[PDB]
Image (cartoon, rainbow, N blue to C red; front, side, top):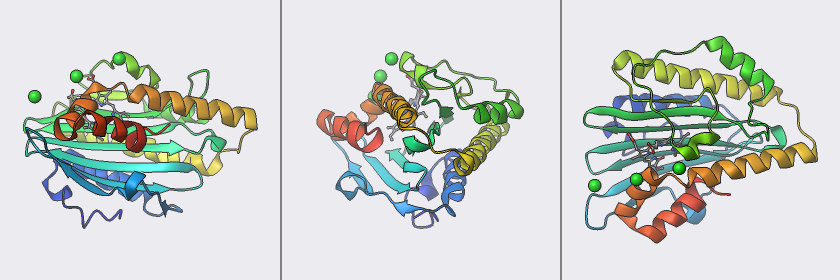
Length: 242
Ligand SMILES: C=CC1=C(C)/C(=C/c2[nH]c(/C=C3N=C(/C=C4\NC(=O)C(C)=C4C=C)C(C)=C\3CCC(=O)O)c(CCC(=O)O)c2C)NC1=O
Ligand SMILES: [Cl-]
Ligand SMILES: [Cl-]
Ligand SMILES: [Cl-]
């Protein structure tokens, strides 16, 4: 569950990943949650082929506003830690997609990505999100990274950095906390939408999932531990279900 106290991975994960896992779990803990059963009621899985083992712990929930809320923690061998999180919105409410991805090795966090990604056909976040996000101001990060082409799905507020030091790690986690606070508040005040608008949002979410499946960084990690067929099933059915 969301206490993370019974997580076997948590104690061994990069400190920034631990703090973000805790912050996400804390944001969700008091919501009107129900379990969301992944395919094959997946929770914990491990695999190895010719190289290192991959271990994944899945936690997934749902609420009336969020069709699927996934928090995945993973580790490859002793050298690679990953946090994956997506809140998939119920299209009826027109909310954007919260996502984040953190990858860390022995040298520290290599990649930290977080966004509230659009679902509208105009590729804009709803007005209330634009207002609240603008008020946070532009955060300063020394080592920004450019998104790959499939990353056109992310908003103009997307963070994609290599944190340079602890100050930046903590600044990133705080900005994710800020995104979550905005998002959970907007989920309370969101107007239920028309059938045509609901359809528009559904389309946006489908596109998001299809584009995320183009990420060969995820796919290679899965393939090296479980093979091509397993990775394709995992990405298309577990992570980014259409
Ligand atoms: C669950 C298993 C899972 C694995 C194995 C995983 C691996 C993974 N994701 C990565 C990058 C990345 N990951 C993302 C983004 C995301 N990815 C997401 O799953 C979500 C929700 C977003 C954004 C909200 C982006 C944009 C990159 C950079 C891709 C690139 O450099 O080509 C990288 C490369 C890190 C680096 O270049 O420093 C790895 C190894 N991510 C995972 O989530
Ligand atoms: Cl691409
Ligand atoms: Cl690659
Ligand atoms: Cl390799």
